[PDB]
Amino acid sequence: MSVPTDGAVTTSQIPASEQETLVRPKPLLLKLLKSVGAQKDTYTMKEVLFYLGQYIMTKRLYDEKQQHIVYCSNDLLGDLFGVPSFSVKEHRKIYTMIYRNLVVVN
Ligand SMILES: CC[C@@H](CO)N1C(=O)[C@@H](CC(=O)O)C[C@H](c2cccc(Cl)c2)[C@H]1c1ccc(Cl)cc1
């Protein structure tokens, strides 16, 4: 392994091949990723999701009493995704929101 630690989350809702896509996060997204330990400039989509999950957890934006919804209207995450809230269960939407904040590599 070339980095000290790594993380990745996958879902049955997105095809494997898509989750392996290599991407280069734009400024705001890269800033959030690094605030939780990420150290690179290029990631696979599943790594991006891992760190974003970590970001949500650390900022305490995840509560089961919120019935699967994350409320990020007052967080930079709300501006990254461009929505006031979203469901952690709707993965295609999450992917779509994330795609706007990056560029696919080569
Ligand atoms: C916020 C907690 C976070 C912890 O990693 N999490 C989950 O708790 C679950 C929610 C679910 O049970 O469906 C999975 C979720 C996830 C995994 C892989 C791909 C995607 Cl799009 C979402 C994933 C998640 C949810 C949102 C984001 Cl932006 C990134 C990752």
Image (cartoon, rainbow, N blue to C red):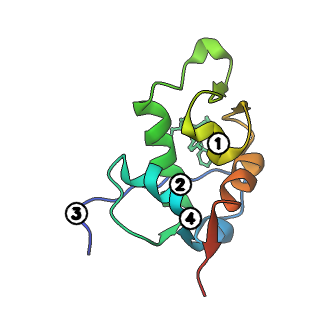
Type of amino acid under label 4: Lys
Earlier residue among tags 1 and 2: 2
Cα gap from disc 1 to disc 4, whole angstroms: 13 Å
Tag 1–tag 4 contact (CB < 8 Å): no
Q: Residue furthest left?
A: 4
* Residue tagged 4: 26
Q: Is mark 2 on a helix, strand or loop?
A: helix
Q: Residues within 10 Å of mark 3 (few under 14, many from 20)?
A: few
What residue lies at 37% left-to-right and 47% top-to-bottom? Answer: 35
Q: Is mark 3 on a helix, strand or loop?
A: loop
* Residue tagged 1: 79
| Left or right for 90, reference 70 | right
| Left or right for 8, reference 14 | left
Tell me the quadrant of the picture where the C terminus can be found: bottom right
Q: Which quadrant of the structure image shows residue 73?
A: top right
Q: Residues within 10 Å of mark 4 (few under 14, many from 20)?
A: some
* Residue tagged 3: 4
